[PDB]
Amino acid sequence: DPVPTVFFGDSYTANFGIAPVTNQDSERGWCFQAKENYPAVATRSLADKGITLDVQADVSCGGALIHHFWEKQELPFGAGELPPQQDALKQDTQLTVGSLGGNTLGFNRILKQCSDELRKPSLLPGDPVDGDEPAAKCGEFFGTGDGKQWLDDQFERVGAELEELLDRIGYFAPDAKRVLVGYPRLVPEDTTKCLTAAPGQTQLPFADIPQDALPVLDQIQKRLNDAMKKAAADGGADFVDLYAGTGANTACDGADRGIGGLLEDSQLELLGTKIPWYAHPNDKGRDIQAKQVADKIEEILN
Image 1 (spheres, rainbow, N blue to C red):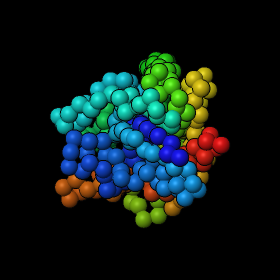
Image 2 (cartoon, rainbow, N blue to C red; image 1 turned 180 degrees about the vertical axis):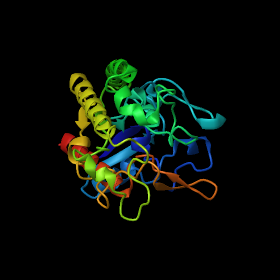
Image 3 (cartoon, one colour; image 1 turned 135 degrees about the vertical axis):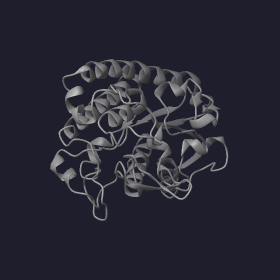
Image 4 (cartoon, rainbow, N blue to C red; image 1 turned 45 degrees about the vertical axis):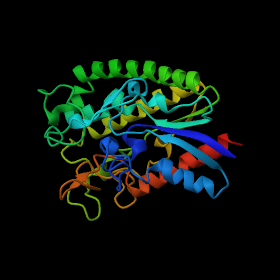
């Protein structure tokens, strides 16, 4: 029995950094949606356990904010405007899975704030929150400064928009089981580990980000995780808590790492260049994602 499914989301579903990309040569090339993202791999796995997903659309795309679910996404450099992701839903859609949220909080703006290196031209969307405040001071800015209230404002828009995401799904695909996928843990409980470069790497997991800012960044990820859990519980959705189980598969777990480093090379080649991971899941991280999601779908379909 086919289970009509829609995959949606941001760079953590599109799996920015994994190549080859789908639609290489068309407008959606700028989505940086790998051919083998967690949705692709989860369908495979499930198929050989006998769960047959009839995938109707996989509209995840890098840089998607929560409201891109209901608004047009503008791709970089004039590629175009993509239709709202909600448009992929059908009345007969029975399963919807994706990760939306990090870009509404502006986890990218928090990384760029904490790093001068990230403040120079890159393929990571966003602007520092306080661009005059200095990179090196970022763990103060967010903990005691202006950043600290900025965060409570971002977190309030997040809570409101996730509820709205969940209600629009409910509205267009009334029979759909909703699966909100969480983000993998970026920084480990023991930050000392980030002080080493990963076997074979020359740059540190988080480049120039002050070591002191490292535990704040995790605090903020935890938070976003609790916001996503809540939103799902209150909205009738299921949640895949990737954060709780990637505690030893962070960006700082050397060779067991499931997050490529900030400046580490991804598999993405633009002219004759590798594009950095920018802290997105790597191959290992993508298999965890796949495994955990496939796990959860299986559970829910039984």
